[PDB]
C-alpha cells in the first residue's frame, strides 16, 4: 500500500494522452525510455514500409487485459480506427485505417510518411473491441496498464490493485490509493503520516516535513510568449484581428528575448524549480544544441533595437516611424503565478523602453486576442510533432497552435524532411534546423517567433521509504508522475 495526493480526478484512452492518468490502468503498444528511445511493451515487432505509408505491427502472443480477456490484433485495430472516429479528441489527420492481418498482426495505413507516428504507438492506450463503451452492468474499466480498478468514489478517492495480467514490469506496490484533496488537507494528511506521496506546486517555498523528502523531477512543461509575426490588418474566420505592427518587427522579438533574465524568473517566481528555456523543446534530443543565448543583457537588447531604428522617444518608449513600442501581453486569468510571471515580464522590459500592458481573461477572451497580441502560453511535449504545431505554416491559427501566424517556407521544408525521415533518430537533424539552418529559422538567431522562458520542474513530497524512480521528463498534464510507475520501490 501507498497513498497519493497528486491531483483531482478521465481515464479513457480515447480522450488522448494530454494527461497522464490513463496510464494507471492502460497501456500503449510502446513505452518511452529515459533516453527517448522506445521499448516495446505489447509488440514483438513494428516496421514502417519504405514509402512510409504503411506500418506493420506484430503483437506478442501472451497479452491479456486486466480482466483476463485476450488482447489481440482486433483490439489494436479497433483502438486505432475508433480513436480516428471523426468527433475525436485525438489528432489522427495522417492516419487512414488499421487492418487486422491475423490475430497477431495489424497493418496501419497513413496518408503520408510520418516519423512521429512512433509517438502515437507510444501514447495511445489500447482498449477492448469487445468491452470498450459496452456500459455493461458491474463491469470495471478494462485496460492493459499496471493497475486495475477496485473502487472509485468521486470527490474522495480511488483504489487500484496490481493488474495480474500486466505485460510489463511490476513495481513493489500491490495496491495504491489516490486521494483527491485540497492542498491544506494534503499537507495535514502528509504530516499525519497518512500520505506517502504529495504533488506540491513548484512555486511553493516548501519546508521540512516529518519523514518526507522533496523530489524535483524534470518536465517538458514550459512557458513562453508567442509573438504576432505579421503586421495588423487581416482578421480570421471568426472576425478576430491578426497581426501587431510592433511585434511584426524581428528586432523587437530578438530584443525581448535578450533582455529577459530567465534564470532570475526561475529563482524568483518558481523558487528555483525551473530552468531557462530558449526554445519550446529545451532538453530534448531534437533541440538545436546552439539555440541558447546569454540573456538578461539589457545593453545588447538596446543595441539590437537602435540598429533596427527603435529610438527612445520623449515619453521614454521606443519608437520607429511614429510607432511606439507599446504592446499588450495577454495571459489566462485565475493563476497567481502566471500573473507574477506576466508582471515580471513587464518589469524586465521597461528598461529597454518597451511598454508592456497586461490583460487576462478566460480562454474564450484570450482566443479573441491571441492573434493580435503577444500571449503567454504553457506547452511542452515529448513528441517532436510539437515543433510542427508551433511553426508549420499549415498550423497557422488552427486552435491554439501557431497563433502568431508564423510562416517561413524553409522551416516548412525542414519540418517536412523531419516527417519524411525513416526513424526519429534520422529526423533529429531536421527538427534541429527548424530553429536555425545556417541561414534562417524560427529561433532567436532567425525569426524569433517566440520568447521562450522556462521549463518547469515538477515537485513532490515523498515518504523516506518510497523511491519514485526515473523516467522520461514528465509531461505537461495532471498525474504526470505515473510515467515512472513501473519503477517505484
Image (cartoon, grey):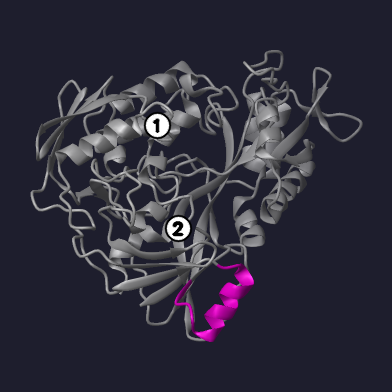
Query: Any mark on residue 362, and which?
Result: none
- Residue lying at 43% horizontally and 74% vertically, measured from the top left: 3
Q: Is residue 305 left or right of residue 485?
A: right
- Residue lying at 69% horizontally and 24% vertically, measured from the top left: 308
Question: What span is colored magenta in the figure?
Answer: 181-197
- Residue lying at 64% horizontally and 19% vertically, measured from the top left: 230
For marks 1 and 2, the one nearer the N-term is 1
Separation of marks 1 and 2 at Cα, in angstroms:
21 Å
Q: 231 and 70: which one is in front?
A: 70
> Residue 450, position in %: x, y?
58, 34
Q: 462 and 289: which one is in front?
A: 462
**Residue 254 placement: quadrant:** top right
- Judging by the rendered image, the residue that carries numbered circle 2 is 479
Pointer 1 local density, CA inside 10 Å: few below 14, some 14–19, many at least 20: few
Residue found at the far right of this picture: 314
> Residue 428, position in %: x, y?
32, 36
User: Judging from the image, what secondary structure is the residue with disc 1 in?
Assistant: loop
Q: Point out the image quarter for the C terminus.
A: bottom left
Up-down relation of residue 51 to residue 2 (above or below): above
Q: 396 and 399: which one is in front?
A: 399
- Please say whether residue 193 is visible from this viewpoint: yes
- In magenta stretch: residue 322: no
- Judging by the rendered image, the residue that carries numbered circle 1 is 91
User: Judging from the image, what secondary structure is the residue with disc 2 in?
Assistant: loop
Amino acid at each position: 500500500t501507498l497513498q497519493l495526493a497528486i491531483g483531482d480526478e478521465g481515464f479513457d484512452p480515447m480522450l488522448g494522452w494530454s494527461h497522464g492518468s490513463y496510464l494507471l490502468l492502460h497501456s500503449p503498444l510502446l513505452k518511452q525510455n529515459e533516453d527517448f528511445s522506445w521499448d516495446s511493451l505489447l509488440l514483438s515487432q513494428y516496421q514502417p514500409s519504405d514509402d512510409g505509408k504503411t506500418w506493420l505491427l506484430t503483437l506478442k502472443p501472451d497479452l491479456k487485459f486486466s480482466d483476463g480477456s485476450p488482447l489481440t490484433a482486433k483490439d489494436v485495430a479497433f483502438t486505432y480506427n475508433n480513436a480516428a472516429a471523426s468527433g475525436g479528441k485525438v489528432d489522427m489527420g495522417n492516419f487512414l485505417s488499421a487492418e487486422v492481418i491475423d490475430p497477431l498482426n495489424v497493418r496501419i495505413h497513413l496518408k503520408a510518411p510520418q516519423s512521429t507516428f512512433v509517438n502515437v504507438l507510444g501514447s495511445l492506450g489500447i482498449v477492448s473491441a469487445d468491452k470498450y463503451n459496452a456500459k455493461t452492468y458491474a463491469q470495471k474499466p478494462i485496460g492493459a496498464g499496471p493497475y486495475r480498478l477496485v473502487s472509485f468514489q468521486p470527490g474522495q478517492q480511488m483504489i487500484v490493485e496490481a493488474n495480474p495480467y500486466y505485460a510489463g514490469n511490476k513495481n513493489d506496490f500491490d495496491k495504491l490509493i489516490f486521494v483527491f484533496l485540497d492542498e491544506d488537507s494534503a499537507f495535514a494528511a502528509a504530516q499525519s503520516g497518512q500520505l506517502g506521496v504529495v504533488r506540491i506546486p513548484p512555486s511553493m517555498a516548501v519546508g521540512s516535513v516529518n519523514n518526507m523528502k522533496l523530489w524535483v523531477r524534470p518536465s517538458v512543461e514550459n512557458r513562453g510568449i508567442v509573438f504576432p509575426t505579421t503586421p495588423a490588418g487581416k482578421k480570421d474566420a471568426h472576425g478576430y484581428p491578426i497581426g501587431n505592427d510592433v511585434t511584426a518587427d524581428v528586432a523587437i522579438r530578438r530584443a525581448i528575448n535578450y533582455a529577459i533574465n530567465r534564470q532570475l524568473l526561475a529563482d524568483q517566481i518558481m523558487e528555483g524549480h525551473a530552468i531557462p528555456a530558449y526554445t519550446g523543446v529545451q532538453g530534448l534530443p531534437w533541440n538545436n544544441p546552439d539555440s541558447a543565448i546569454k540573456d538578461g543583457d539589457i545593453d545588447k537588447a538596446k543595441q539590437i533595437l537602435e540598429q533596427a531604428g527603435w529610438q527612445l522617444n520623449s515619453q521614454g518608449t521606443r519608437e520607429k516611424n511614429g510607432l511606439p513600442a507599446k504592446i499588450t501581453l495577454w495571459y489566462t486569468s485565475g493563476d497567481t503565478t502566471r500573473r507574477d510571471l506576466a508582471q515580471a515580464l513587464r518589469s524586465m522590459l521597461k528598461p529597454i523602453g518597451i511598454d508592456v500592458d497586461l490583460k487576462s481573461g478566460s480562454w474564450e477572451t484570450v482566443e479573441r486576442n491571441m492573434h493580435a497580441n503577444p500571449t503567454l502560453f504553457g506547452w511542452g511535449s515529448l513528441d517532436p510533432m510539437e515543433l510542427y504545431h508551433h511553426y508549420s505554416s499549415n498550423a497557422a491559427g488552427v486552435e491554439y497552435y501557431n497563433p502568431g501566424y508564423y510562416k517561413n517556407p524553409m522551416v516548412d521544408k525542414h519540418l517536412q524532411q523531419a516527417l519524411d525521415a525513416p526513424t526519429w533518430q534520422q529526423a533529429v537533424p531536421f527538427w534541429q534546423q527548424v530553429d536555425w539552418d545556417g541561414t534562417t529559422g524560427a529561433g532567436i538567431r532567425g525569426d524569433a517567433a517566440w520568447a521562450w522562458l522556462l521549463n518547469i520542474q515538477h515537485t513532490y513530497l515523498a515518504n523516506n521509504c518510497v523511491d519514485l524512480g526515473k523516467g522520461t521528463p514528465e509531461i505537461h498534464g495532471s498525474w504526470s508522475l505515473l510515467n515512472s510507475i513501473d519503477s517505484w520501490k
